[PDB]
Amino acid sequence: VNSFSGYLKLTDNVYIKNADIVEEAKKVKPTVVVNAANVYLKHGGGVAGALNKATNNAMQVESDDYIATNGPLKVGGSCVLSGHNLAKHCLHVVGPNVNKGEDIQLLKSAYENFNQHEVLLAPLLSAGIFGADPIHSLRVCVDTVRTNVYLAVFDKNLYDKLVSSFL
Ligand SMILES: O=C(Nc1nccs1)c1ccccc1
């Protein structure tokens, strides 16, 4: 049993809810919250900007030190950093950004990072300002992630379309 409430069950291991991932993280304090990161861990907008704002910029300060030591992530890659006030850990995952011309086949590689964690609160990778089709992102998620993933979808209209169209 876990703390996640109000989710619709899509599969054995994937759950979905219309929710603000920031507000959900603050309520649940999950072991792992996933960030929709870029390779520079520059948390300007979208899910990343919202998560970072909720940490009062502490996520960005920690991220800048990580990049200064390690250099940029790979598209499709990830790193584990603090969850600050939102979670124990933040898994920063880089999905391909269609608005930069990145290979959408890298979306499966991105979701494979989730399999290193038994339970996660996450957004749909490469959705929103990363430009991918969220219906496609949900299909890759279901077909790639084997661990237990609780997906937060900010937009109510999109949430209803994802559920209604789910095969
Ligand atoms: O945003 C999209 N679909 C949405 N439906 C409801 C709210 S947003 C999208 C983005 C890229 C390619 C195809 C579709």
Image (cartoon, rainbow, N blue to C red):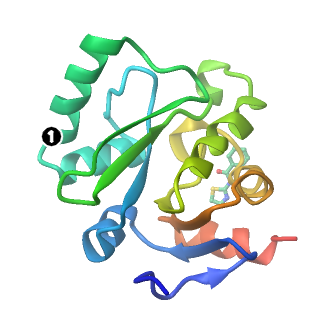
Viewer-closest of 113 and 56: 113
Horizontal and vertical percent for residue 35? 42, 46
Tell me where residue 109 sits by quadrant.
top right
Q: How many marks?
A: 1
**Amino acid found under the numbered disc labelled 1:** Asn
Write the residue at 75% across / 75% down: 11
> Which residue is nearer to you in this view: 99 or 62?
62
Residue 25 picture location, percent across and down: 32, 66
Q: Position of residue 65 (x, y in %)?
A: 20, 21
70 in relation to 117, above or below: above
Q: Is residue 31 left or right of residue 54?
A: right
In this rendering, position of residue 91 left or right of residue 94: left
Q: Quadrant of the C terminus?
A: bottom right
Q: Residue at position x 32%, y 62% from top?
A: 22
The residue tagged with tag 1: helix, strand or loop? Answer: loop
Q: Nearer the viewer, residue 65 or 8?
A: 65
Q: Residues within 10 Å of mark 1 (few under 14, many from 20)?
A: some
Front residue of this view, candidates 103 and 120: 120
Q: What residue did someone put label 1 on? A: 57
Residue 6 placement, left or right of 68:
right
Q: Which residue lies at the image location 29% right of the left edge and 69% below the top edge?
A: 29
Q: Position of residue 103 (x, y in %)?
A: 74, 23
Q: Residue at x 78, y 77 (%)?
A: 164
Q: Is residue 122 left or right of residue 21?
A: right
Q: Residue 17 lies in what quarter of the image?
A: bottom right
In terms of image quadrants, where is residue 98?
A: top right
**Residue 95 to residue 84: above or below:** above
